[PDB]
Length: 169
Image (cartoon, rainbow, N blue to C red; front, side):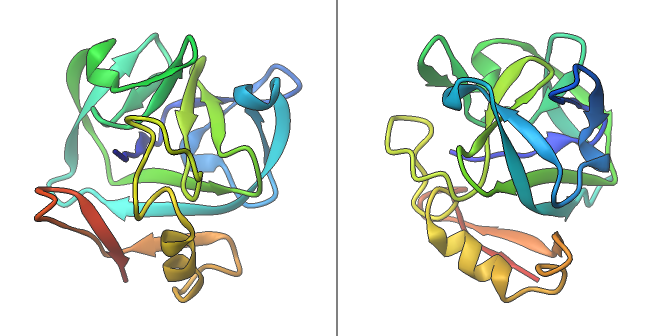
């Protein structure tokens, strides 16, 4: 599956400070727990507008609001956030996703959140579009790619019912 983050979620940095998701930019270094907490560079930030201005999130700890199917790695296994937290609704103009240069997970609010283009094939992590270079090549054609910030228009879905098949701009 896939998902996105609320912009107020706090991304762990290597100096022990935190940055909100909505402030992360290309060239920032985030922590990839699966690479032994090594730092990896952000290649592109992807924004999707919240049509109704609110979205259902799962809250994990104090510092992470994440859409309910966004894969997270807990004790070696990929899980849905809905498995681990209570659902809440939050106001959101945009929700956020990231393309990383390598590693393809990042520590947000203490949880290991999967990113785009990740090539993982395990259950839950696997996604034929979002976990392959297909999404990256699409993003590469979009406005914002070189600057590292792409606002997509819609996540086109379905009959893999509700499953994202294309980002379009």
